[PDB]
Image (tube, rainbow over all chains, first blue to last red; front, side):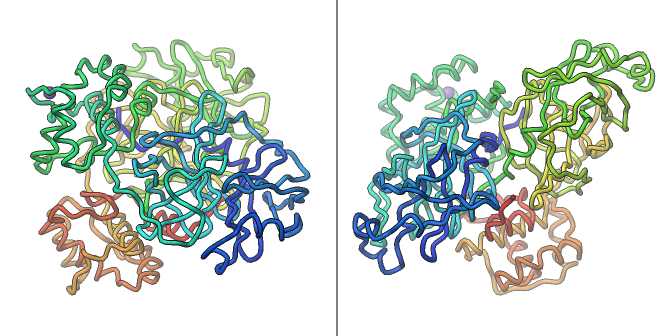
Length: 306
Length: 306
Ligand SMILES: [K+]
């Protein structure tokens, strides 16, 4: 029994984290084969950041301007290119600990593990959701940039996020490993508003299913609802619209528990309208939305890796 | 900067997890040097479990009764001993991936990362507290036993927990790596009651400090209190007494924020009595108690590992 914010095991990613330094800026890089990936803003000074011309700043850089340290081993940079907002430093050594990996672009609502690093060394691991507004509510400090988010399938690491910046609101933004930001953000120190953050409805439902599996059934009610009637109530409480695709993905959990998706939707409707009356679900007084349907299945069925 | 249930990186522990099989039972073992540690109840059948005489059950066992698999590599058992409730299988091979480690017995309140495993293979990693009643509110399924809890200092893994059993209440119990149960529990299938669980006061305070660091200052009040006056209020809300040792360990955070421990205590007093008025601290509507003072320092200062 029990249910936790459970992260993927970090071992495979630990062995890819390096320190990258340029000028006075030190952040993290991801070392896969003979390439180190890191945020390109590492080449910028404080003043460059206000309006950086990256094409120009990079032409003015040479390989020796980049210091890459893997543990107590200096990696020599022998090449550099830029892909969107990621810097690719070609190094003299293929990472012996390179795992099987893919670069994946995730959708809002999907979750991943983050290996928060400083100076190429891991500080911790935690589970995360890509928020609907394309931010993530991470735990990152100065120098966290280059830290990556990932999922694991079997033995294959699917890298989906690289951390680039913190916004004034204290939430975080970054790119896929091709250097394309998630959301309407740029690696420039210019005012940038997060879109309004909404609650990931399908994930709340998934977590309610988790709660049922673990006993909690008090929120189950006698009501039912149509999909559209639900979404009308949801929108009023800043909940993402629930699509048919979402309903379909919840199918496995609806089958496991025997509770139909729209029935669970009704249970949520009431919770939104009335509240919880000081009661808690899976130890939480708030409706948790950082667990996907698949995440519940994985934790409740005991899926392992490598 | 944000705040998350953040686990230690699992890499070092991943490389120590093996599968151990005996009779009708498969669970997990921890492979350090030429020894594999696992719960001794692996030698029991269903019938043995009702009233096991372990000294006698083990005398009747031979090395060949124990099948240890590290991936697709069979480890040959060449010896067996019992230390309290842990079985130590001596094998023909020292684990090449043995990290620097200690075996530590933690105190109630203290936290650790758990690497949940099935069949010697990791499913995930999550942060945990040793509850005051010596249970842990884990996420474990059938076959999780042998899974370990740990902290890391620099490069040294301090193993503090091995999972042995789930109790009727759905919470978990186990031993230090010397095989001594935490709490009044035994590795017998006989009814066993968890003591009443209390809230880990020192940890709630630590987490309030974390909240200050991340902005939230609304719960700060002008009032102060003596230690005893605080504990009188605490006991009424099922909070662990706050000791002077607790005050001392909160020292770093009190220094960092400039808020005195007893001042923070007063702020907590009010929160306990009046509630939050539907407000939230670090995204939570409940007072969180599974973060130690050190855990907050590590997350908020960016402490890394190896
Ligand atoms: K219902």
